[PDB]
Image: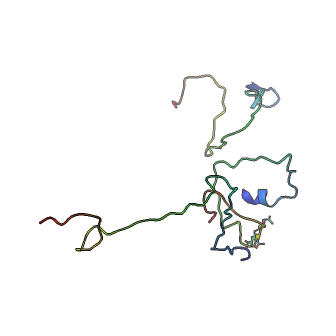
Amino acid sequence: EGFNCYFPLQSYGFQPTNGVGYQPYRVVVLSFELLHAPATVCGPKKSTN
Amino acid sequence: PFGEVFNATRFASVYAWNRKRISNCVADYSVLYNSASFSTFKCYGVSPT
Amino acid sequence: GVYYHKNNKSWMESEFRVYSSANNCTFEYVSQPFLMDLEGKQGNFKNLR
Ligand SMILES: *[C@@H]1O[C@H](CO)[C@@H](O[C@@H]2O[C@H](CO)[C@@H](O)[C@H](O)[C@H]2NC(C)=O)[C@H](O)[C@H]1NC(C)=O
């Protein structure tokens, strides 16, 4: 970590007092493949005769 | 002509800094750190490399 | 301004007060070298530019 050596890891300064923009947000991404195979996952419905 | 600015006998004070003009010529970055070993080199909004 | 001096037959600048000074210069340049005739003799225009 001398000259021409820089640290990959970084640390936040999260505390209540920091600006609104500087506040930490928690993000949950949801991804899914576009129905390529007859999968199972989907919502509530009714089996019609 | 960065070398003349970079290697100078005396520099101005912080209250009366020297403003200069670089126009219609070509700069470089590889001639900054090869044994320069300055205190701090960094850039904002773009990687110095 | 050019003058015909009797002591030396040549045409020197007399008053180059075209301007006062320059606050700042965005750009400066010198064009490729070439030469001039510098003759005051009367006559029809031997060249067109
Ligand atoms: C201005 O300073 C730099 C160093 O910051 C000098 O550049 C050196 O050039 C030679 C070329 O082989 C090498 O030693 C390095 O590339 C540079 N310096 C060092 C210390 O390694 C430059 O010549 C200086 N100008 C002067 C003294 O007029």
What residue is shown at x 85% (from left), y 54% (from top)? B11
What residue is shown at x 72% (from left), y 56% (from top)? B1
Q: Quadrant of the C terminus of chain A?
A: bottom left
Query: As displayed, is residue C28 above or below residue B34?
Result: above
Within the image, what quadrant is residue A13 found in? bottom right
Extreme residue in the bottom direction? A1
Q: Quadrant of the N terminus of chain A?
A: bottom right
Residue C19 falls left or right of residue C32? right
Query: As displayed, is residue A45 above or below residue A7?
Result: above
Q: Position of residue C12 (x, y in %)?
A: 76, 31
Nearer to us in this view, C6 or C12: C12
What residue is shown at x 72% (from left), y 47% (from top)? B21
Extreme residue in the left direction? A49
Nearer to us in this view, B34 or C36: B34
Query: As displayed, is residue A28 above or below residue A6?
Result: above
Within the image, what quadrant is residue C4 found in? top right
Q: Position of residue B45 (x, y in %)?
A: 61, 56
Within the image, what quadrant is residue B27 found in? bottom right
Nearer to us in this view, A41 or C10: A41
Q: Quadrant of ligand 1?
A: bottom right
Residue A23 falls left or right of residue A30? right
Q: Position of residue A20 (x, y in %)?
A: 63, 52
What residue is shown at x 66% (from left), y 40% (from top)? C26
